[PDB]
Image (cartoon, rainbow over all chains, first blue to last red; front, side, top):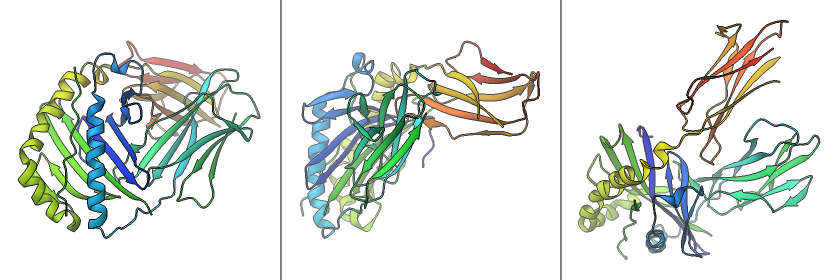
Length: 182
Length: 190
């Protein structure tokens, strides 16, 4: 890769079919700054603070997405319709900070080698589904053009409690479960 | 104060399928040296690219052969300019006042796994210095460390290990230095 003190990712767009799935993001030094919510047609910052000074017109993201929709049809044919190869995701779970009983912490599930960029990341607490208090980053680009994604689970440490990060993807015969314990 | 996007340019008109556009702006010593790169990707193959270092579109693979010719005849102008309206502008007017000023102080804690683990968490930016100490003396062996870990939430973490034998009365210290810190942080263990 190229060397620099800093690196900004601008205009980052992804589009695929079937399904009309598109994504537009910006990153700086490897971290997501925002993504444009295609549905609501709005800029969603990774951190609240963000869009308080600087600004981004969602219109831009929508443009690139559309252009990419255009490019996909052409290249698809050009390749004599060569499909995307389903990769197998690799998942890892680790705590944000040192674990202390009864003290609010966060489990991070890092998933890499994602391709195509369609995936189901879920959490289980004692093999019981958990939907509340869960956050998920956008699909973040890798130099090899695959993606990585992160999910977060805010929890209260306690002994014996078992946590799982469940990953589902077409390139997976069976779903993968990444376990973590207090 | 407005962020400029790096624009995707239209190709000439001639089971899952994927296409990607990557706009990249490299910076070294402020905006002293800037470099723009634009990648056009089909599935996982980059076939078309524009690079400031070159100044024009080049085919990365046989798949982009003619794409290069088209983009060069149709967009050379609009593209080269993004180096200023996108890279230079975004850096000077949007990153300087935000990301380049963000400072997160690390949290430091020592726990015992024998092996000692100094956990240095939630700091930003990535530049950090961590060293172990036994009785004011620096540890020159039995020191290992995890890779720098990106939490994905704009904070980093790193665990620095120390192999040792808890001989009574000994005093271990984890020394941590980071731009956010007024003075180094030191946590002790006995």
